[PDB]
Length: 180
Length: 180
Length: 51
Image 1 (cartoon, each protein chain N blue to C red):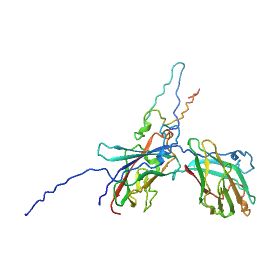
Image 2: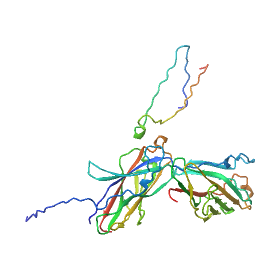
Image 3: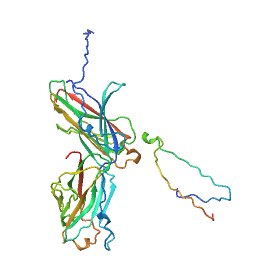
Image 4: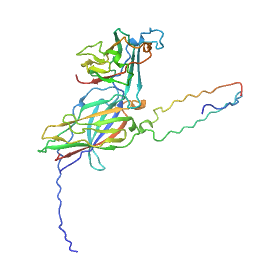
């Protein structure tokens, strides 16, 4: 009864995102042992073909029985957006499974240069114990820095200690915004 | 308003830490009395199951009313990291309680072979009177040495003098780095 | 299972020994290539001149 339409159009323009990810400084640690991988932090990306995400993988070397605390892994900052951005981290879960996930007794991703409310997402093996952090303000040009933290349970099997076997793959979304 | 995500990945590789702890030389003092424990310094480790730390316990024999000054208890040096390391000590507090803690009138852990700024953490019974030391440089292969110092108040009860009863358990973190 | 019973062996004929292995399929993929050792068991077989 008395229905009518309005017939909208939608036009989509495409551009490069204004946030981007930058490789920090610890990737140039340039010092390593006889294990093949001759670095300690890898920062790189690869276009996922299944769903089209700009996935940026990070490889961190974790030390058995000794907590490890990085400081400069990723740099987040806008190069195009003239206002004041807002950033936050959200945890999701593990990607894949190698059944070694129960040997990661702790794992944290946290802001370094600017700080805020809780300011770290924490994984307890496979589960998640801290979902999201607070927001942080990024202006035009200056960059916030993201560190890392890992503690591998020292009961790790010997064969998986030579620095090759991957023992975890954690999902960490980086959600930007334009309001606090 | 105008929010977007970036969807990072994190890959973790595991390896043995490059610092490690070494048992020094005073552990081979090989000379002792009729008390059961037929040594003067014990150096050993045990994988903590609660939180996965590579705890390295140390047993020191303290002499009543007479300060004791060791020289070679622990040796700290890298065997894998090709650069120039940096080490420092941080005190935390006591572990457990036996109510004898008030009879330790002094306790110091200090570098021996290389030296630096304050260069000793000091416990006054249960409290802490010197939090952290300065940094010291360890290169590839050569080792820094950590001594000890203890002074037991001679009003100790007689029954706790036979060298069995443990009268203290002090937390001493050893924090490494890659920058001074 | 602590130990087995005795068995008689004569000159020339031999008692042959089998095996039975079952590995939980939840084993991590990185250790399935066959290079890695997952166990090391000691069993002592005891000769005797009496049953």
